[PDB]
Length: 50
Length: 49
View 1 (cartoon, rainbow over the protein chains, first blue to last red):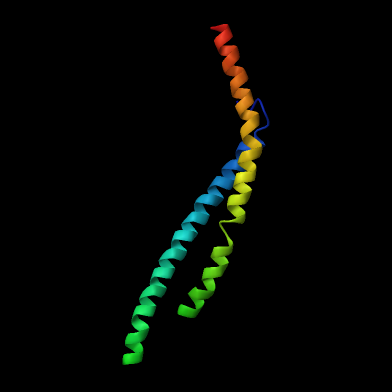
View 2 (cartoon, chains in turn orange, yellow):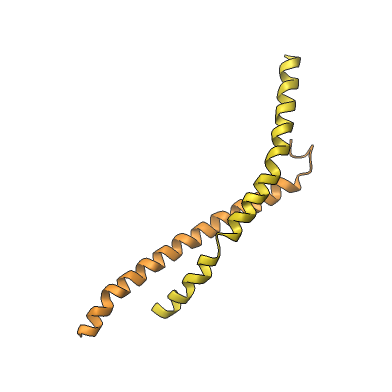
C-alpha cells in the first residue's frame, strides 16, 4: 500500500514519531532533573543551617 | 549544578510544542488521503466478494 502511493510520507511520519519519542524521553529526563532540583531545594535550607 | 539545570529547563520547555505541532500537521495532511484510499479499496473488496 505504501509503495503504490509515494512512500516518502510514511518515512517522514516515522521520523516525526521517533522525534516525538526521544523528545518525550528528554521531557521525562527534564522532570527527573526538576525532582533533583526539588531535593536541592530540600537541602539548601540544611546547607544554610550548617 | 542547580543553576545549570535551571538553565536547562527552559530550553527543553521550548521543545515538545513545535515538535508536536509539526507531528499534528503531518498527521492531518496524511490522514484523509489514506482514509479515502482505504475506504475505496474496502468498497472494491466488498463489491468483489
